[PDB]
Image 1 (cartoon, helix red, strand yellow):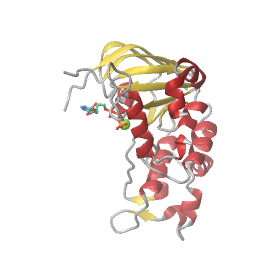
Image 2 (tube, helix red, strand yellow; image 1 turned 120 degrees about the vertical axis):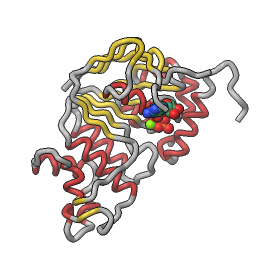
Image 3 (cartoon, helix red, strand yellow; image 1 turned 180 degrees about the vertical axis):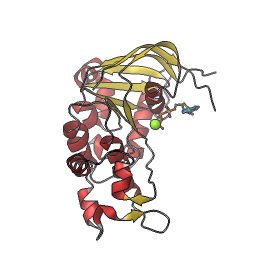
Length: 254
Ligand SMILES: Nc1ncnc2c1ncn2[C@@H]1O[C@H](COP(=O)(O)OP(=O)(O)OP(=O)(O)O)[C@@H](O)[C@H]1O
Ligand SMILES: [Mg+2]
């Protein structure tokens, strides 16, 4: 596994009056630790992860890690073929690794709904899963793939999936306990159980540290966000956006 180091990092989006997508980003994450990244819509959570992978070039500062990454996108995707083929996806088959992954990702119930189990063909002529089941497969695919560093721009966080709590506890927390990983998340339980948390807004880091430090350093912010996890993904992201937007020389009425 690996360590991730960011030091005074600034980047601009090359493709496609506000300029940099990410500004003065500073964090270290120890081997086997979890970073929870939370923040407003368009803060730059996906782009931070892009930058770690090499998809985005920094104009300032250093990025350090081993360079063996598995990335999960926030958009569920499915290749034509079996559920099993979608999780394995060109990677060497191991029955114990696969089983523990599909268990952690809460797919065992879904799979057993089918007569062919995980050998059911998904696609054009086959069957179509719910966006929720497709999210579980997508995370499983990214987690089954072996890596030093796991960038989870989780599809949950923009979905309301009944069994997400179980995914986070079993997969991200326990199955992946010895992996260095980064979870983009809109849930407060995830921030509480993380080793480190990062709050991003308009390209900037408005907080980096632990949940304890957050609760202590910014209590008014904390009390506004920490039953919050019972709200829908769309609603939680709104409240977060609304709250983060107060960090300015105005801050509107509602
Ligand atoms: N490949 C790209 N090329 C150019 N601009 C991009 C690219 N990806 C993202 N951006 C821009 O950078 C800004 C921040 O994007 P990003 O997707 O990182 O936000 P985010 O925090 O992931 O938001 P959300 O929570 O809605 O996913 C956005 O305004 C977006 O238009
Ligand atoms: Mg994103």
